[PDB]
Length: 106
Length: 106
Image (cartoon, rainbow over all chains, first blue to last red; front, side):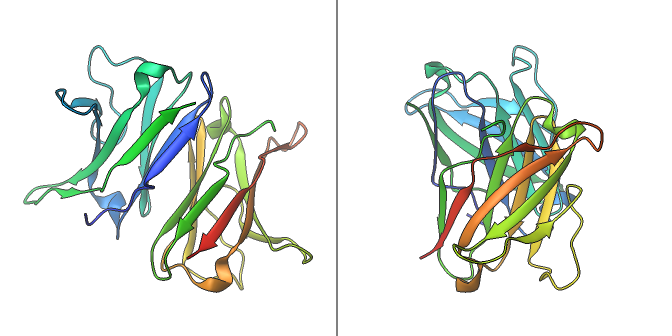
């Protein structure tokens, strides 16, 4: 992992969860965020810093400034529990990866 | 209580720590960050989202977007161990406050 993420984030149902991702000059790369439930297909939730793919709710938002990219999830529910991974792209590349954050909804 | 921060963040010396601060439409306000060691004066480390007072190490940076403001400390030192509190100002309405994050180095 060349990108740093908190190992874990915990929130109560309905609270907003935020997950950070840091690296040197991360802001000059596009951040991508994946929701990964063990044994299931990864889901891209945010791309190019702040863009939501079709089918991803306005609940999910992202930004990338300076050395830190942040994914925010409002109105967290149980089905948001997963590992979240950031990656930074630019090309001519290559993708650098974060270590993952376990999100628990208590 | 108005803004939400993680209860704690733990890092090893030299590692990057980030602390989040969330609230509805927080991104439309100015975020301010205070470092507070018990029994000492609070120290303003970041103001107006990303601005750094003189005397504050360049290791400290911040940003604010959507519903989340983020304080980042690169190359964390034992001296940085403290409680960190976010606040948000409308420069027209009353400040709203976060509940504080304990940063432990080690």
